[PDB]
Length: 262
Ligand SMILES: C[S@@+](CC[C@H](N)C(=O)[O-])C[C@H]1O[C@@H](n2cnc3c(N)ncnc32)[C@H](O)[C@@H]1O
Ligand SMILES: [Zn+2]
Image 1 (cartoon, helix red, strand yellow):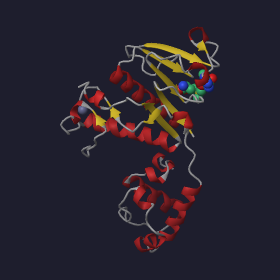
Image 2 (cartoon, protein in one colour; image 1 turned 90 degrees about the vertical axis):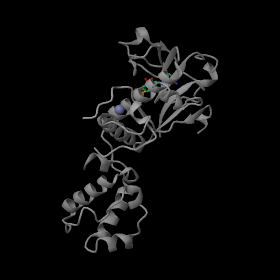
Image 3 (cartoon, protein in one colour; image 1 turned 90 degrees about the horizontal axis):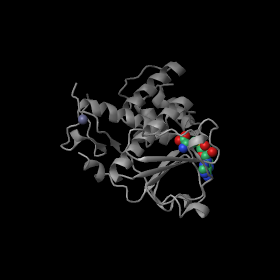
Image 4 (cartoon, helix red, strand yellow; image 1 turned 180 degrees about the horizontal axis):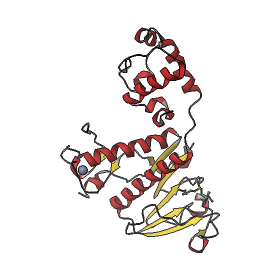
């Protein structure tokens, strides 16, 4: 019911687990137990045995254990609008960072039928392609079905963007989001990072993370604003990974290029 509990349990935080205990107490009329009965995150919860659940909660552990197994068997369907917004947030983050890091002069947006830039304030020439452009944006979209066998010698300037545009094989100069390996041989998996160049502001649980690429993290003292934004971005990113999307990137992508922007 709480949005985080619609993620796969491996994504649950320690607070998410506690909210799970409360949701389950109401849903199954269980004896209330201390919010600290399972002080761990979901990754840890999944390593417990059923005996551990029974020892930890004599009155309800077996039920909680079986509930978790039911959740792992029938994963919660996500909300389509929330997942769309999440994926869009990630798209903007990732493409903004790529352009800042490598200063591509042209972006080839392949599989974009609406001619909408995810990063409209970047200094880059944006070009759109789609096999079936929306008829109200086709005037500025190249009608093109991409196949590596036909186009691998094209679009070699700048960077290519394939945001959920499933082609036979991506070219090496690509940013890719794919929903569920030979399509990806020219690329590498893209690890999580958060980048921001917005002003730092101090007015939380201090954020410690090597993947918060902000000016205030150069010295390890993340400001409250970026702590907040990092955590919101991580929630959006978890919701897109938990739904089956994965990110891939051109092999030269380097987060130190982002640090150097400061
Ligand atoms: C999930 S939709 C929209 C993807 C878009 N990049 C986005 O972020 O919303 C997939 C799009 O890719 C187009 N498409 C699928 N295969 C394609 C291909 N091989 N070459 C060009 N466009 C393709 C479809 O016509 C459609 O507009
Ligand atoms: Zn900051």
